[PDB]
Image (cartoon, rainbow, N blue to C red; front, side):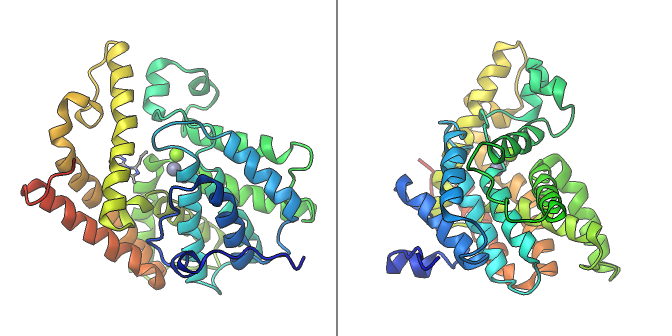
Length: 316
Ligand SMILES: CCCc1nc(C)c2c(C)nc3ccc(OC)nc3n12
Ligand SMILES: [Mg+2]
Ligand SMILES: [Zn+2]
């Protein structure tokens, strides 16, 4: 009960900032997550023994892929921590419990392939889940780990609270399907602008939590340029492997996934920042003003990619 996690001073201070990088020391990541749950939720939220066993089983079920890995899970959870800490009074006790766990679990058992590759391969998961294929799998894996003996971090919740928290986690994980993001943001845009956005309307909260999940999931574009640029390499390493696997199925991949077309990456990043990232953080800032640093950092990195194109710097 009286057993706090404390981080070294530079981490203690920087972990509160949106652009925090969790660093290369894997063995500190569980501690960083527990630290974040304790300050965001409380030292009472979870039984430490059960939380630590849950965290280590979650880690075990992330694969050794270049980007969609344990480091991505903890990174996406830290962005959610920063949003919750900068919006103290807007979220319920159950939301704070659920969203950090949802973020940690959102890409469980990812193989580094898109839903589209699963459908073209005719992967069994694509027969079991026709839309948001990988995201229904991630939620399925979350439930599995929660039902291992000693792993039910929610055991002290009531029957109805338990059902509410798993429903928060399910919608939160489904929302990380970027195919659902476009429509979800257009509606939040309309609702905000016509002044009809109501945070007491559960269907409205659902949409806002969905956009927060997109915001955290994309948060590599909100880091300092050297982090953003080095993470882009890992992201494209997965895209090129999928492109290789498309070519093996006798399908020419889109240029984004073709490793012979690396020269088109800078222009592909512009497209992505303009079509997805900037709109995401803009609408998020409108609904939650204290998340403006994410938009500012995203704009700084768009400006860095424009420089790459004008050959004023080369990404190695
Ligand atoms: C599944 C990966 C989604 C994702 N997360 C980040 C941070 C990114 C970035 C920087 N670039 C992307 C360019 C295209 C794309 O196409 C889906 N997804 C991208 N992406
Ligand atoms: Mg995902
Ligand atoms: Zn993700």
